[PDB]
Image (cartoon, rainbow over all chains, first blue to last red; front, top):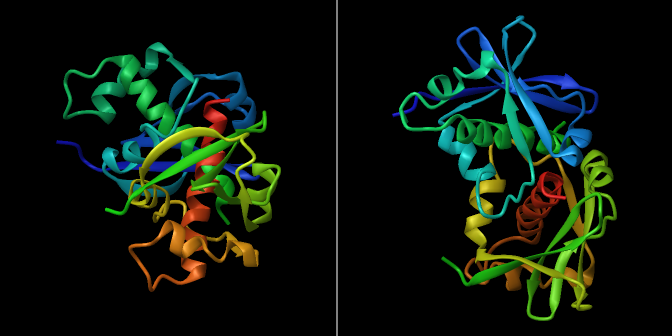
Length: 124
Length: 124
């Protein structure tokens, strides 16, 4: 299982702040600043209504992203939490894996989103 | 695949500065600040005698890394050059691909090192 997931972004200064778009909802981190967030070592998820101001980045299966960002090379001290609004994340992003705990879902998607933001520093 | 390579790093506080150790030589980017390197968009490769200050990160075949960090999402805007001392890079890191050009070799290893160095912000 697992329909392709859509990575989207907004420009934030000289990098990109990423989200996963599922229907008319965007899951992303409540992070004002990527370097601050990285050094702080924790983030909260938010799920927002799509305001029409996101840009498409990449559509691919989850595995495409997890393979690169949830792996043995990519160390992380980061800790992810979420709001009540975000408890849909497991069903929305891992529809094929009925098992998946909420802290795993957050951990996986959170590493993808922060990793993408960090590697946006290499982009045009 | 090919023989395993050894990913190594120096902890520079803000970030971990990654290299590839082959024997007593480390290939890495002549850059003190990964943020500067990323935004400036060009780097020079150097090959240095092991000064005993490197930390072991990971051992894996080259392909473990290339297959992740050379991709359609992050691209290849970055420009690499190298010192004359560093022209051994193709032979040392790609023994299995004897026709591989130097600029392809620099491009591939460069994207691995930039990616690991940027993603180290999750960890430090």
